[PDB]
Length: 143
Image (cartoon, rainbow, N blue to C red; front, top):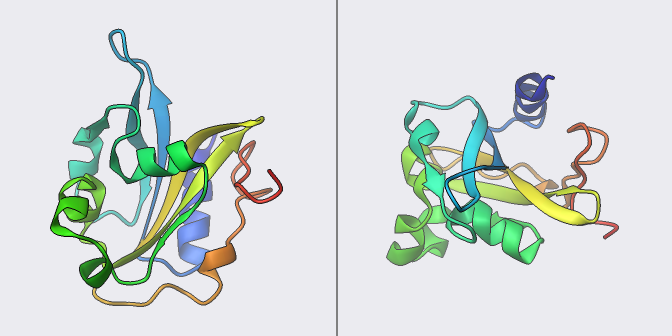
């Protein structure tokens, strides 16, 4: 209440083509990660993404608890990497920053900021800060 709006603000203000939030959800005998919120999406395929623990770009970020930066998806990610990151394929991202969302002293979800069509990541994305901009969540800085 309301994460969609905040997501739009960040994407609109920081000038990204795409933004999304990954959060934990209850599954049968296993918690899963889904892309619950999205801004500037080109289709609705991301809604169908269900990730087992540790999997996907979101899972990589949740596991390491530190941000992941990809200036150029095409050149930096292997075929295997790309296949294992469905939202990247689904949204046609050519560059992206993924940031761990921390609730309390625990890594919780992930914020993805992405670009399309070869548009570079905005200058300063490397030290983008979640705190006081996404409700309760903070990033890995000061952890």
